[PDB]
Amino acid sequence: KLVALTFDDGPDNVLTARVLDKLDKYNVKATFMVVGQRVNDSTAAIIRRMVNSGHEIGNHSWSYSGMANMSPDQIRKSIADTNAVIQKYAGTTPKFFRPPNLETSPTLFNNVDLVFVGGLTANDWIPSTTAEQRAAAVINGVRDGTIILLHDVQPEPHPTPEALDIIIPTLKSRGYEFVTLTELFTLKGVPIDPSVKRMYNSVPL
Ligand SMILES: [Co+2]
């Protein structure tokens, strides 16, 4: 039984390191869907720390704008510029894309050559919700193959790192193992094929 823990909306040197510290504590791998505007010399080391620690990096666009109604040139620029900064500091190229706001269109699918991922959400962008509530949303929603969509970066209070102290032990005790997105596809025997123009919330579709 496999799940993929994924985190949007960083990197942030302070908030992302809180998530990375919990993943180090439990020796778990995850995937970070990063925003190009945030990837720069100040955040180079923490982006590299993801790679160094066995995590994967995917693309969450240059910024925080929905992309469904953008033009092909706007889409291409946003994805390419984000890939270029990830390559500079991480030395890797994304295979996966998470659309801002999970909003898609045929034009967006047509102009992004990455595998689109969504996933099970946990209301963890709502500061009034507690660590325990965020954990309960995840634990009760997963199944074998689920992609879990959390945020490493949001306005505070943001007790997502604290939710991991419940999510990770609970799911392990139920027989789950945590994997990156690439590992999830590979271990399930699903080609990571960007010509598939569907959004994956789990693997297999
Ligand atoms: Co986002």
Image: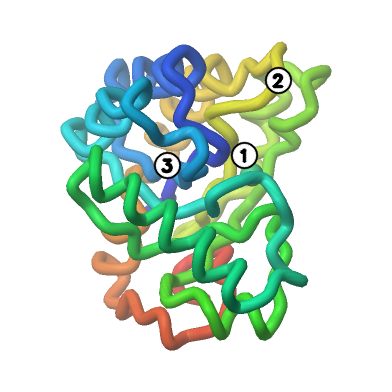
How many neighbours does mark 3 have within 10 angstroms: few (below 14), some (14-19), or many (20 or more)?
Answer: many
| N-term-proximal mark, 1 vs 3 | 3
Can see residue 203?
yes
Seen in the image, is 71 located left or right of residue 128?
left
Q: Position of residue 37 (x, y in %)?
A: 51, 39
How many neighbours does mark 2 have within 10 angstroms: few (below 14), some (14-19), or many (20 or more)?
Answer: few
| N-term-proximal mark, 1 vs 2 | 1
For mark 2, what is the residue? 155
Rendered view: 196 above or below 181 = below
For mark 1, what is the residue? 138
Seen in the image, is 132 located left or right of residue 32?
right
Front-lying residue, 40 or 108: 40
Residue at 36%, 21% in the rendered image:
42
Rendered view: 71 above or below 31 = below
Front-lying residue, 175 or 181: 181
Q: Amino acid at mark 3?
A: Phe
Distance between mark 3 and mark 2 Cα atoms? 18 Å
For mark 3, what is the residue? 32
Place residue 106 in its image quadrant: bottom right
Which of the two marks, 1 or 3, is nearer to us in this view? 3
Q: Amino acid at mark 2?
A: Pro
Label 2's element? Answer: loop
